Amino acid sequence: GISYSVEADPDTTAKAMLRERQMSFKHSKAIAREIKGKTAGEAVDYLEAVIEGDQPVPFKQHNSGVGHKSKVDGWDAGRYPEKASKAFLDLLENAVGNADHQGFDGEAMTIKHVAAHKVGEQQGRKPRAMGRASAWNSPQVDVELILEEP
Amino acid sequence: TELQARGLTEKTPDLSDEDARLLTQRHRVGKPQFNRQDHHKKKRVSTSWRKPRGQLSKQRRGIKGKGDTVEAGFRSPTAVRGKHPSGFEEVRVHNVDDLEGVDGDTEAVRIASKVGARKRERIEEEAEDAGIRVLNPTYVEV
Amino acid sequence: AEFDADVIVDARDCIMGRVASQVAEQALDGETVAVVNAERAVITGREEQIVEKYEKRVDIGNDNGYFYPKRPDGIFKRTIRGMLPHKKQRGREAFESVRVYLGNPYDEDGEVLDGTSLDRLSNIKFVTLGEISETLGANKTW
Amino acid sequence: YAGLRTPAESFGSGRGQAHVPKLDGRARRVPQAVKGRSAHPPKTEKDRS
RNA sequence: UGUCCCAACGUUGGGCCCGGUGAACUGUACAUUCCAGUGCGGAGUCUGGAGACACCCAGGGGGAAGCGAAGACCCUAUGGA
RNA sequence: CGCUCUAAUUGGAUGGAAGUAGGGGUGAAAACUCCUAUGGACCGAUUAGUGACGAAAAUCCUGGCCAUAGUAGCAGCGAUA
RNA sequence: ACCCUCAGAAGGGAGGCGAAAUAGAGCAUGAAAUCAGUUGGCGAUCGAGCGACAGGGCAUACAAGGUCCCUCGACGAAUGACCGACGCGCGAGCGUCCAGUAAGACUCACGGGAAGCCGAUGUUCUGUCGUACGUUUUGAAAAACGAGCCAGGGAGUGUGUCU
Ligand SMILES: [Cl-]
Ligand SMILES: [Cl-]
Ligand SMILES: [Cl-]
Ligand SMILES: [Cl-]
Ligand SMILES: [Cl-]
Ligand SMILES: [Cl-]
Ligand SMILES: [Cl-]
Ligand SMILES: [Mg+2]
Ligand SMILES: [Mg+2]
Ligand SMILES: [Mg+2]
Ligand SMILES: [Mg+2]
Ligand SMILES: [Mg+2]
Ligand SMILES: [Mg+2]
Ligand SMILES: [Mg+2]
Ligand SMILES: [Mg+2]
Ligand SMILES: [Mg+2]
Ligand SMILES: [Mg+2]
Ligand SMILES: [Mg+2]
Ligand SMILES: [Mg+2]
Ligand SMILES: [Mg+2]
Ligand SMILES: [Mg+2]
Ligand SMILES: [Mg+2]
Ligand SMILES: [Mg+2]
Ligand code: NA
Ligand code: NA
Ligand code: NA
Ligand code: NA
Ligand code: NA
Ligand code: NA
Ligand code: NA
Ligand code: NA
Ligand code: NA
Ligand code: NA
Ligand code: NA
Ligand code: NA
Ligand code: NA
Ligand code: NA
Ligand code: NA
Ligand code: NA
């Protein structure tokens, strides 16, 4: 798995990670990209709206065939990745909790750094026509999050 | 409180007029990179030189713009070939005994990278006392 | 609107190509040029064949397109563009520092370039850009 | 016999594959094949005196 | 008698948008092209021009002498059956 | 010029070897060498030998990996639940 | 180990051991292809063998390179004048003299200047040249054949005889 790729001052910082999550790595890059710079609390509200379907996540890189969304500003394609979003909510719940156990005001902290990394694939095989089988795998994702005092 | 290199770091060699002229020429003229053809088009093809052999190779045929082909005509002046840019002739050194016979006016010494700090210290102090410059000196805080 | 032209050229009764060739040369030298009275510029030859050529250019085209100007305005400017490497940075810079005008929006009267004037008293086979545009279907806005 | 203990055969043309002896869909025997024979190996018969 | 004149409207499953799952084919490189020319005589890439702000969605498949298969035709081999 | 191991002669290394990454110098070049970080135990030079000794290619072999793509399929069957 | 978190013997946070956890369990080292984030350069008006050689922008901790810029002056190969004087030509222009002079690449010396400053490196812009590589072929950029990319593997060897 990963290690934190950015330095973090322990006195004004809180950390968290997800390990080998079986979820879309592409949905993860998009989500991380969108919530960085946000407040922990803002991020939580944002992802809940995504899960609810009232807020789209801009898909700027993995957008082939993706329909346009009116709420996406400065871009067109977007979706509502609920699974990856739920995993991020778990990530934030942890971070904010770690933050609190350290004396900070979790929710109010800024997401200084957030990033997903594909750590592997749970390999699978799908039988096909003509007596042949082909790959049918699941991405495994690690993700780091660093909260920092305003 | 600051880093200082050991030895005669500033020392320069004394060269005949003709040698300094040829050293200056080499530095002015230079040479082409002489990297293998198309090394930049394929990652699996490294920079290390290989004679282009293709019957149709544009470089092998000498087409302008496809890079120079290695030839003896590109050789550096005999009198200066191999000299450190400073004009000194290098002498690879592994220990204190290697310093024996070395002309500090004409040669500078390069301590092999494998030599440890304990032996480098001895080599560096006696080289300086022999008037020999050490191209790769230790930097101590003084 | 407002064009700090370092040179204001009068095309009235002048050979379009000979003017264009000079305006090109000058714009590539850094000069900002304005061609005045384009509609009154002229080209030698048999009106019938001349017009056929320009008419052919209008009809040429396809989805990719071949936008050929009909007004004496653009005809002249396109003529100049053909004497400039308009796709290179330098070429486009020069071309963009040249503007052609119908009539004269300036106070000063432009100058007449050497060897570009046509003597109407010793020439009968020639045509006016304005006439060409009228034949092409342009809207005589002059 | 290192590398030769196999009945691997080449399929020949037809499947967009190089003509290399294969067995159980795995290449074998030929020198460019992993697990294949050594083309010109050291030999006992050589007079080293 | 919708085979046709000559096509229309409708029904169900898709298609389209959303959650989840999640391959393959294919890939020398570069690549926004078009008209002509040239070239081993069938060029996105050479030459001259023309056109060309970037990204994305849906479509029917004009081109990549598209992908798929070391041509079955034909000849050649001091080949095979 | 470079690679393996042998021999003689002779050196380096826990005061940090090999390897790797980035960087400096030399050689027309094969390639040599130094610095910094990583690494944490081995490594050379000269001479005479040795050879399962040098790859961009073989629809080459094996493994890994990107685009393809969040795309095709997860509808079609007289059993539509 | 303990504590916080969690649906939780998961995972995460904090913490503990050890020279080292970036030695934490398929765990020595940890290349390339390649992915995430991020830095430098370019960037939504513009053209494609991706470069070589020249030359500019912008970027750069140290180390292992230390040079480079401008005045002037010295030297100065080939080449080599303007102006002016005189003489020709219808004319463009030429001849003689000034003069093989002034000039003239490199190199050096005095004085002055630079430390992102010179080299070098990354990227980008401009100029010149440029339709991969290997093979087949009289002729390959080829609408002839091969390869998605990278790493590792992958082809004159032995005995006998003869020369
Ligand atoms: Cl993925
Ligand atoms: Cl030589
Ligand atoms: Cl058109
Ligand atoms: Cl141009
Ligand atoms: Cl006339
Ligand atoms: Cl010189
Ligand atoms: Cl041979
Ligand atoms: Mg779609
Ligand atoms: Mg079956
Ligand atoms: Mg390369
Ligand atoms: Mg084997
Ligand atoms: Mg073109
Ligand atoms: Mg065939
Ligand atoms: Mg037959
Ligand atoms: Mg037969
Ligand atoms: Mg010896
Ligand atoms: Mg080859
Ligand atoms: Mg493979
Ligand atoms: Mg598709
Ligand atoms: Mg029913
Ligand atoms: Mg390890
Ligand atoms: Mg032929
Ligand atoms: Mg290899
Ligand atoms: Na995209
Ligand atoms: Na939008
Ligand atoms: Na919007
Ligand atoms: Na004319
Ligand atoms: Na037209
Ligand atoms: Na066997
Ligand atoms: Na033997
Ligand atoms: Na019907
Ligand atoms: Na098509
Ligand atoms: Na293949
Ligand atoms: Na540069
Ligand atoms: Na061939
Ligand atoms: Na070729
Ligand atoms: Na062709
Ligand atoms: Na593939
Ligand atoms: Na071999």
Image (cartoon, coloured by chain):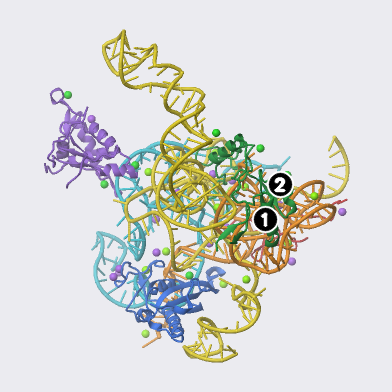
Chain colours: A blue, B green, C purple, D red, E cyan, F orange, G yellow
Q: Nearer the viewer, residue B93 or A115?
A: B93
Q: Is F13 located above or below residue A142 in the figure?
A: above
Q: Count of labels shown? A: 2
Please tell me which residue is depicted at 58% across the width and 36% down the height of the picture: B21
Pointer 2 or 1: first along the chain: 2
SS assignment at label 2? loop
Amino acid type shown at disc 2: Val
Q: Chain of mark 2?
A: B
Left or right of G85: which side holds B87?
Answer: right
Left or right of A48: which side holds B115?
Answer: right
Q: Is G87 located above or below residue B67 in the figure?
A: above
The crowd level at tag 2 (other Cα within 10 Å; few <14, some 14-19, many 20+) is some
Residue on which disc 1 sits: B124
Q: Chain of mark 1?
A: B
SS assignment at label 1? helix
Residue on which disc 2 sits: B102
